[PDB]
Structures are given as C-alpha cells and as structure tokens.
Length: 362
Ligand SMILES: OC[C@H]1O[C@H](O)[C@@H](O)[C@@H](O)[C@@H]1O
Ligand SMILES: OC[C@H]1O[C@H](O)[C@@H](O)[C@@H](O)[C@@H]1O
Ligand SMILES: OC[C@H]1O[C@H](O)[C@@H](O)[C@@H](O)[C@@H]1O
Image (cartoon, rainbow, N blue to C red; front, side, top):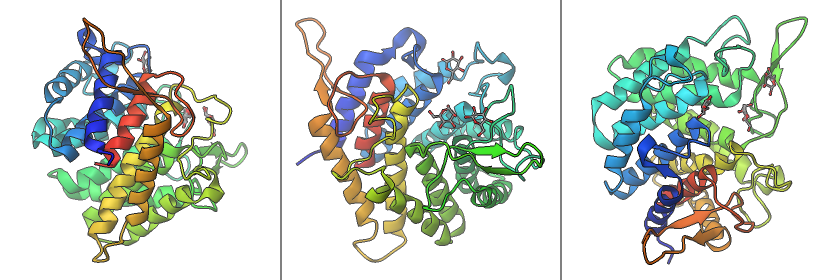
C-alpha cells in the first residue's frame, strides 16, 4: 500500500523546499557541487520512470546555469568539465538520463564533451590503464571515477553516432577494471588503487567498501549488456549485487537494510550521506535488465524485494514531514542518513539518497 511515485514526489518537494536555491539554479551551495548533479539525476529519473514532467522546467534551469564555466575551474570551459573527473562524470551521466528523458540531442552532446574531457586523464603508463580522479595532482586512480567513466562510455556505445569507439573504450575499460584488483575476494569493490614505491605496480588499497562503488558499476555493466547482448556482463553485475545483499558482508543489516559502513559510528560525512541512493537506483537498473533478459517471472525478484524492503524501512523509521504554515504551504518529506536508524536531521545529500531509493521502486 506504499506508493513509491507519490513518496518520490514528496521527497523531491522536500529537497526543493529546504535546499533549492532559485537565484543559483542549484541545491545547497554549501554542499559539494557534484551532489547537485546526483540530485538532478534523481529528479530526472523520477520523471523518466513515473512519466511526470512536473520538474522539467526546474531541471532545465539547473542545467543552463550549472553548464556555465565553473568559477573554480574556468579552464574546463563549462559543460560540466570540472577540476575532478568524477565531478564531471556525475553530471555527464545526468545528461545521458536527460537525453533519455527528452530525446534532445543537446544533452547527448554534453555527455560526449564530458567523455572526451575525462579521457584526457586516462593513462596506460600507471596501473596499466584507468583514469585519475584529481586532475590537478594525478595521485589517485580510484573506483568511483573509473566506474563513472565506464558507465559513461558504455552509455554512449548505445546512444552516440560514433558508437563503436565508445564500445571499444567501454570493453577495454571493463577489462582494465576487472584486472585492476579493486574487485576483491568477496566480489565487492574497495575504494581504489595504491601504487608500489619501488616497482610501479598497483594494488587494491583496501580502503572501505562504499555502497555507491557497488552501484555505478552495475549500471555500467547493464549498458555493456545492452551494447553487446552478452549476458556475461549481467552475470558479473549480479555477482556484485548479490555480495551487497548478503548479510555476511555487512552492507546489509540483519533487518535486511542497506547500511553505510560509517553509520554505526555516526560519522557519515556530506559525501557518504548520498551513497546509498546511488546504489539503489543502479540496483533497479540491474533488476530491470535481468528481468528483461529472461522469461522466468521470478527474474530479478530478489533485487526488487530488496529495494522494497529498504523502502518500507526508510519510510517508517527515517522520515520527517515539513510543518506547513499559514503562509508557506510547502509540503514534502525529509530524510536522515540511516535507512533504519532514527531521523535526527536532513541534509541535501541525505535527501538526494532517499529520493534515489523511492525512484528505484517506481
Ligand atoms: O564538487 C566539488 C566542488 O564543490 C564546491 O561547490 C566548489 O566550491 C568546488 O571548490 C568543489 O571542488
Ligand atoms: O590509495 C592511494 C590513495 O589513498 C588516498 O585515499 C588518496 O587521497 C590518494 O592521495 C592516494 O594515492
Ligand atoms: O567518502 C569516500 C570518498 O572520498 C573521496 O572523495 C575519494 O577518496 C573517494 O574515492 C571516496 O569514495
């Protein structure tokens, strides 16, 4: 009796009432800019899955202003080309979804500019491949920038005119990622690569297993499946998702709820607060691809039940409503970080993550 389209809309209204800045065409300028890109993704995906165009004018406004040359990275020349490859990647994938929503080639073109910009920091000369996250310094090849890159080139292999260079890049990037060692012995992805002092060989740095690094990779593999019709991409994706769902690996509580490793210590910072909903949206993409590739009705049923289980927990334990007034009639729902633990306060990243979970259930 829970309607995920209605709750997604109420969560987007809450996001807007507390965090949207009209004069800036952005949410929460006091929060990292890439998380406005994630938020835009969630709003776009709500519209795609539900069929609403309620927020289209707002999204267009955000795109128009945020595509301008960034005051902190003018040499990027706008179009979301930023001072880190992952920041660019979040907006690039938002533009892929906006293209999917509208069919407007402008958004696809932006994604193509973003891919060419990110590729500049791919090297074969360290780690046999992959790109750096930190453009100014070039010290870290990490999971998230390389997952976003992979999902972007794979997305373009299905949509762009010069589709075969993107397919070759996606297949080579997946080959590199699989061979990097970041996917560990329980099929989960650690934070990134360290580099050996004497030898230049790279290895899994054993930094934490973050939920969004188990999620963006699933979307990439789903796009590789669509570009190739090779289910072995779905089989790898399902292995990573199945590891997340397994309570033995500690991302899934004994209540069956998705749980960031920092929640226990109450230490989730502004980045980590958004991670879970990015995983959920990507898990929904995997579940749709698996159910479509198979005649069995129970196909992808575990992923769908998982998202449902998480949705009901967040709805019941992690929710607070804006108090309407005589003057401001704004309504919506607000959310904290723990999809099981109690609501203490809302932040823009926490809210974006919550919207992601509802949209994953539409
Ligand atoms: O996305 C990260 C980005 O977010 C902030 O809004 C900006 O001030 C930048 O300095 C920073 O690099
Ligand atoms: O794994 C190596 C890596 O660890 C840190 O988390 C990063 O900030 C990088 O500067 C460094 O190269
Ligand atoms: O919050 C964790 C997050 O922190 C930084 O932004 C980078 O080191 C990422 O690789 C990492 O996932």
